[PDB]
Length: 162
Length: 162
DNA sequence: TTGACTCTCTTAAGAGAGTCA
DNA sequence: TTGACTCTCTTAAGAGAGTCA
Ligand code: NA
Ligand code: NA
Ligand SMILES: [Zn+2]
Ligand SMILES: [Zn+2]
Ligand SMILES: [Zn+2]
Ligand SMILES: [Zn+2]
Image 1 (cartoon, rainbow over the protein chains, first blue to last red):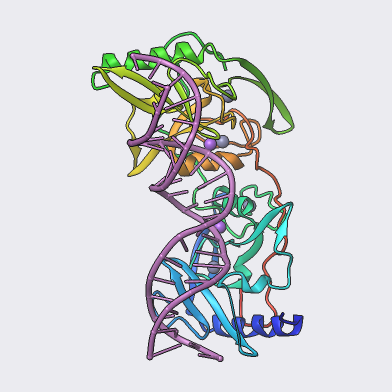
Image 2 (cartoon, rainbow over the protein chains, first blue to last red; image 1 turned 90 degrees about the vertical axis):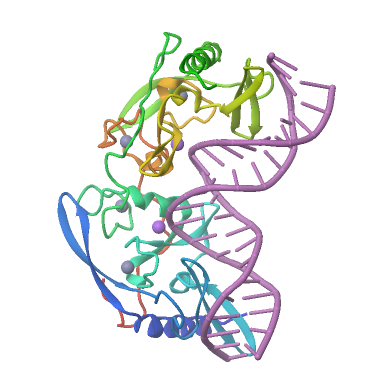
């Protein structure tokens, strides 16, 4: 198995490569009607992506390194967290985009949490709109708002009470 | 079936049957430290479920009626909304449990909205904690809270900015 | 050892349809 | 006609692994 020193070297090589990804400035809602700026380090749309990187799905990538003749491969956003626990409360930890930008690999835009916690950030009001996440959101979730409900609760007769 | 009269008759028979489901009182967080009470009309755990109802998955059911000598069948929570548009902004409309209780078939606890709006209610602070849903939530979402994030955003070197 | 492709799987909110009796 | 089972699919946040040169 890899030593913790070998893992750190993988993280370091990953950071050096992602650091050369195009850095894109995005203006984003923070909640409370305020706007902020995030700087995303975006993997390219098509090959080549960068040393060690390959696309396994439309918006999925993996990072691969060969150490002492053994090929090791990780989800491309999981590498910052290789020295962290991989589960919590019986749930698998997942890479969670605080910037909600899947191509971004900026580790300052990622956290490591259950898939439920991950998903829920899509609807968060944001760091200036009432976010209660202990690891605070960087922006208002893209799906926050009143929604677009087509039909509300209703009955034709009188069989029901709320 | 095809005619509006036939659809109204389906809705009316569905309501009469669901109206005979056991009524279970559930005390629920509303947000803001307040508590409320909902009356869920719960489909039984095992057969028989009620006239027209059958279980197609651990927590999935369907409602079936014979009209024009043919069998018509729907997801068991979709029946209240058979006269509504079945899509919005090009997204499929789905039955959304405001009570977050899958066995409940109380139409006063259901709305009809995109799967994204549906999911997002799991994290809503609730009607007394800041819900902004235009069709208002009945309770705080079961997954609302600080989360259990294992690791936050971090870098080893100096390649990244937020 | 490396790049650029290929394939299927997980989760938890939701669906459609077939086989029998 | 009605009941009680069986199966796979959709979505959008996420994953693991094989083949070839
Ligand atoms: Na996410
Ligand atoms: Na729901
Ligand atoms: Zn980013
Ligand atoms: Zn948040
Ligand atoms: Zn209910
Ligand atoms: Zn709400």
